[PDB]
Amino acid sequence: FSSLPSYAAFATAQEAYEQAVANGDSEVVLKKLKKSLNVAKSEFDRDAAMQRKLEKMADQAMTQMYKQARSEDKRAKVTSAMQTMLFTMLRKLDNDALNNIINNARDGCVPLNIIPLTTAAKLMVVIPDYNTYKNTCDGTTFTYASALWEIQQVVDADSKIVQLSEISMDNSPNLAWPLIVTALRA
Amino acid sequence: FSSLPSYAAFATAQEAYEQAVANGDSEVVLKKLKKSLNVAKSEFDRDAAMQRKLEKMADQAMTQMYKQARSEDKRAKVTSAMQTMLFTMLRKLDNDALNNIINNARDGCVPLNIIPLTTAAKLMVVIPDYNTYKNTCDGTTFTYASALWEIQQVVDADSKIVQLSEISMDNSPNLAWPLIVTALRAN
Amino acid sequence: LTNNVAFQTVKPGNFNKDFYDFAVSKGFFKEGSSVELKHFFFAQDGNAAISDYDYYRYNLPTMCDIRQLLFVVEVVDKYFDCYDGGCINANQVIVNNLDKSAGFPFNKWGKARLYYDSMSYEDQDALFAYTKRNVIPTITQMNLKYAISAKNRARTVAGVSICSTMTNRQFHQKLLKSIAATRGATVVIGTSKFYGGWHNMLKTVYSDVENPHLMGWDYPKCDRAMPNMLRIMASLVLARKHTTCCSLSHRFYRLANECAQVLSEMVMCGGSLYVKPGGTSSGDATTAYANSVFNICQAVTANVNALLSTDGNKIADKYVRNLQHRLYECLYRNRDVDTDFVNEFYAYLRKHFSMMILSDDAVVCFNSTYASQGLVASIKNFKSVLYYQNNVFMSEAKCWTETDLTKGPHEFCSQHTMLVKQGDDYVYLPYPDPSRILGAGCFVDDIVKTDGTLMIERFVSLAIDAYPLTKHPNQEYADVFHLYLQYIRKLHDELTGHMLDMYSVMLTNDNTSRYWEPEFYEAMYTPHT
Amino acid sequence: VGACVLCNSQTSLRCGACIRRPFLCCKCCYDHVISTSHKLVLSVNPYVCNAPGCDVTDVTQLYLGGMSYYCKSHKPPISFPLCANGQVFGLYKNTCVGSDNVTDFNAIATCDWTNAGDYILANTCTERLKLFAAETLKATEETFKLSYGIATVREVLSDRELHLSWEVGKPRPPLNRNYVFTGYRVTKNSKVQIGEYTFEKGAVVYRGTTTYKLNVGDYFVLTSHTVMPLSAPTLVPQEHYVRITGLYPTLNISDEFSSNVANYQKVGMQKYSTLQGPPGTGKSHFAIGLALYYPSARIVYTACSHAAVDALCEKALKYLPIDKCSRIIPAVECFDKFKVNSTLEQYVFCTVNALPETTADIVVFDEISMATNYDLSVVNARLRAKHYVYIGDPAQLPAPRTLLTKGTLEPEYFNSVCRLMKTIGPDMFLGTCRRCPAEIVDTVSALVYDNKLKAHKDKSAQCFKMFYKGVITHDVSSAINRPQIGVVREFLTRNPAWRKAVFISPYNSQNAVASKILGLPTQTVDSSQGSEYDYVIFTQTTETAHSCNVNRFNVAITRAKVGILCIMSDRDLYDKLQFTSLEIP
Amino acid sequence: KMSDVKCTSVVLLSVLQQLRVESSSKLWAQCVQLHNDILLAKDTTEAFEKMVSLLSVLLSMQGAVDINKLCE
RNA sequence: UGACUGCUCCCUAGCAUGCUACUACCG
RNA sequence: GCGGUAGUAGCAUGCUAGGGAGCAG
Ligand SMILES: [Zn+2]
Ligand SMILES: [Zn+2]
Ligand SMILES: [Zn+2]
Ligand SMILES: [Zn+2]
């Protein structure tokens, strides 16, 4: 508004008009600087309204560019954003079964198939070391997804079937440890 | 804008205004000078309103012409694409059996539903379960639509080639089940 | 068409974690709250498009009562009398969203914009005149709908070819625009629910009913089970306006194009062709209006069956008894149209069975003391008519009945009605299910709609749709609109914050302070457009 | 939307008229637009008049209009120039820094990469500008080499004999091993596995390490690769700590060298350590000594070829156990003699051609001199570590010039970091000479190595020099000299005991001609590392200054084991070499 | 809680679809069934069991790094 | 791969109409 | 000192075009 030559001319004309009116002037001398004031006012109110429109349109265009950039960066990082959102919501759920399976997948065993909810279907997991084997398995029972799974078959990474009471602390480092314990829901 | 005769008139009006300001001429001379510049502004108002409108109209007409040319180019491209599609699908018609059934018609006219049912060299069967598989596509060859079809490829919804030995009662839950068996016409 | 079957799946909805967290921050989705998320983007597996296309098995070859159908047609034509229609040239055709798909195989090369640009007005006129003396079978592509819904069943819309749609536009669009330009008519297509339009619609429904009750019904598998006879009747009623622009051969060949393109065409579900047994290909140029005339036909048939399946000795009123006698005469005794009795029965229906018809969604203000006496179809005549003339069983649990008119229709266009006092008088405002708006906010179909800052006008429109919830006696319903206002304020404040972080200053002139204010949305439901 | 190239300011503006579309903030992008012909800049959407059928791209003529950008002839009444107030309109138009130093960018953007000034500016500029210049140089090279058609071969001939033609007006591509053709043959539809070929003078002879099969209808072409952007500069910031904490000191050291561990410990605590070591001359010994002294530091070994590092591989097993030796090959194939199916290992082997994602603790930049800023940046970005040590010497090897026409690269100005490495001198000593005697070590020390190398043994007087004139006559890019070959034959005939060496020549023409008389293979002196033998003979033929620089053949100079003859066609090495002149018939 | 588990099912099926689970017809059909049943469930026990079953699909694959995504 | 129709918001552009604003022509 | 006619520009209204989005059947 006040950063244009039009504003300087308008201010000069306004000051001259105010001085002429306050000091005292005839009709002609005042009308001269009022006709020279109205042209300046028309040129300044048009210029500042154009500047107002330009400022608003520039802000809208930068907002639109921000919207497009955010859209592209959300459409190109969606794979990571959705996973992070899912895990934040999962830890917000603080569900015992969900937390159990998430911690197991983080550290130790991951399911080899979709875990069932019926008491007839079976489950296959991948226990990679003795720590998770001892923490989860206890005798013929396998604790997983906040549920008791009855162990039915334990097979190592070399497709070698092994018994139940054979893997312990000292005998652990003699078999292919990425084993696949098959258990049935109780 | 920059090459109109009103520019010289405006320059002369400004020169006369400077001469009157320096000399201090009478009010009548100033009024006559204003009546010249101000109606030269009338002439230039028209040169900036009719000529500027003509420029906008010319730009609009050029834009419409560009859009029409692009539309005609799109029409040519779509015409070529459709013509090539028709010509490349006609060549797969196997016009031997097609003419055999067309010439056998009363007036060369047949329903569309029978052309693939009589003159198609490849049959695709989509089967939702093994119970429908054993009824329809049993073995390496089967009969359908009054013709004998021999299987050349079986795939699942994953588009993975699945062998005929894998289609079993006990092996059914281990296969994605819309099974798509493709067969060839026998003779 | 291809060597392998194409299995199209439906993706799950894109979550709006920001909006959901803001809602639960405002005390939403509490355990036991009357408002809970019921609308979701239900996902579908590979064999879902074909599974939904198999619902056309409910379309059976149905022979209609021809002496009854020929009178129901006249009554429906009397319903479609105030409108005007006829052929329009290619230059007079209005097409909204020219960037929509164009059936098969035209979708391989471009949208409808290409085929409305590649064809000059003379080309389109020649194509349309070709259909007046030829039949062009077309391929209709079956497309899985990706939208939020409260039902896990896959939704499918019919993608009709540009050849069929372009000609059906030139044949029907004049009548369709006339229908969607008329206010106070039985068909309320084109009548806005905003600016008091919902109140105007409901007041026109309550025209002159002496003992008024509100009654809405449901057509199970409407687009899938509609008999081919009723679809042909719908197209002929829509073709009743072509008395001058078309010859009898032209009208018949246009009907044949309709039947070969949108009634028994080759469907392209998956990547292979199928035969459509019948029903409404609910993607054609006349889907809403054909469904409207079908709905009016079903209502008129139900009224006729109520009148005829009534003991005329026990009909106390001497006018209704004579009306039933002349109804039987005009059905099974009179062979030509009795325009006098057609007008009389149409007036009787308007006086006692006033309807509000959209595409298979309807609200009827019916004379309750007449439907009790069997002088008007209450709900059981509708059930019987659907059973014997639509091959579906209309469950009465899908059909509401409101005996008090101060509370409007229980559900029309998925919008409930409550009588609110805006200004100094009482008006009916259409408020939707709060779960629907909450799900629209929470579940969105693009990832870019997961941050509202990107599309703030989306939540502005949702709050426009959710404003009449503010007047609802249940506080959580009003809390939905208040939550949307607060979320719009949050979105604007975060957009300004992000812009300030990207500038050294912030936007000074906003004028956006009306979006988080009830005044902008109240004006959307006040009778001043 | 990223940091600016010339100003490191957040920006969403890419200079469209440039090659790699660099990120430029508003002020510097405006400077680039007004000071060059790069009148096109990109954004979330390109800066172009969106009115249909318009062809203006100049930002000066482009004005912001409605929801898109227009021009004066197509602007709405509400018009807003894009480039004004010294900055082009865009995002981060207020949070901008800019830079007065835009002349270098405007000069390098419009250069054809054919003048030495471009190389000088690339070597002397900011790190971001240097990386951008390297990326654009690679893009220009791959666009000039792909600026021709597909070389079609219509006939099949005998082994090592193919008549390969050129395009219409296409100049002759480099016949040496500088460009290794890596195409993809098309059987009918798909382009896959043409194989690996190496064009050499026969008439094209291919030397395939492993067997390959050729299809019917295949063609030989030079398919370009994907020029990835550059992130890391040549050098990382340097810092020195105060105390040795958190480490695992071992008790085993190499006792052969007693004056190097005291500085290797500092290398383990200091960032950079420059040593004056010629390639394959005590360079491998430092790595083995560090591995023995510091088995807990993670060391990654890289080389430009497997043949040169084969000597290192053969000795690693004799020095280190098989278990610790591992090679994580990116899973376009090589041998499998190393360990397999073991992700978790300390020492891992790889090649600079294919460097997978990895991390370490100590880095040995083997052959850091023969790698341009593009290669140095690729290794510095694709690999990251906690401690970084730069093993190399500025006076080791000059980079080969491809498109240079005027000007010769100065030996001191190979890299900007190498300029600092040679300013104060090495801070460590390697006083154990298990290599060439003082015949060549002393001569090279008094010349370039600042007389710092150690002379334990005396000069056995096993090096000789010959003075000759020769005749210069080009054929395509080299020369053939009959009298030189005649003199070589006359010398080797009376003493055939020296005819047991693989001849190495900078020009392949001499050995190509002599293959019909002697049968020795042609081995280029640039990549002759890894092959060593007792008897060695050298010949540079011509006397031009661009080939007789101070240290270019230093790779094969120190590859001798008992002594190497020096035939200097120039007068410079006559005064520099302290040897005895011998008669030549 | 119930709305929470339904939204978690939505995001979980989103990440599964992003992981090309739909390339396996049986696996994608099972995931779709579980996701749709969670949204149609009325109690937070059946819904949570189906949520565990659906999450087992994500944990069954090696395409997602479980340690990195657990930043807490 | 992305249908037909209807209603509503927001931004921009150009054009029709109500003003407002001043210079002078004309009596 | 006169009615202006005009004019051409801030302001308002409308009509059209283009883009983004929301709900409904
Ligand atoms: Zn007509
Ligand atoms: Zn910059
Ligand atoms: Zn540039
Ligand atoms: Zn333009």
Image (cartoon, coloured by chain):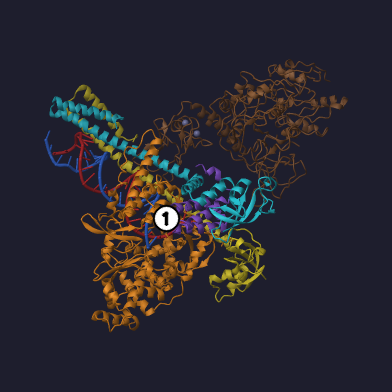
Chain colours: A cyan, B yellow, C orange, D brown, E purple, F red, G blue
- Which chain is disc 1 placed on? C
On screen, residue D69 above or below D517: below
Quadrant where the C terminus of chain C lies? bottom left
Q: Position of residue C90 (x, y in %)?
A: 39, 60
On screen, residue B106 above or below D267: below
Q: Position of residue C485 (x, y in %)?
A: 33, 48
Residue beneath disc 1 = C98
Q: Secondary structure at mark 1?
A: loop
Frontmost residue, C416 versus D309: C416
Horizontal placement of D190 versus B48: left or right? right
Task: Give the farthest residue toward the right.
Answer: D494
Q: Position of residue B92 (x, y in %)?
A: 60, 63
Q: Position of residue D105 (x, y in %)?
A: 51, 29
**Residue B135 visible, this angle:** yes
On screen, residue G9 above or below C258: above
Horizontal placement of C187 versus B120: left or right? left
Frontmost residue, C9 versus C338: C9
**Residue C245 visible, this angle:** no
Horizontal placement of D202 versus D414: left or right? right
Q: Quadrant of residue D181?
A: top right
Quadrant where the N terminus of chain C lies? bottom right
Q: Quadrant of residue D161?
A: top right
Q: Amino acid at mark 1?
A: Leu
For disc 1, does the CB lie below 8 Å from ligand 1?
no
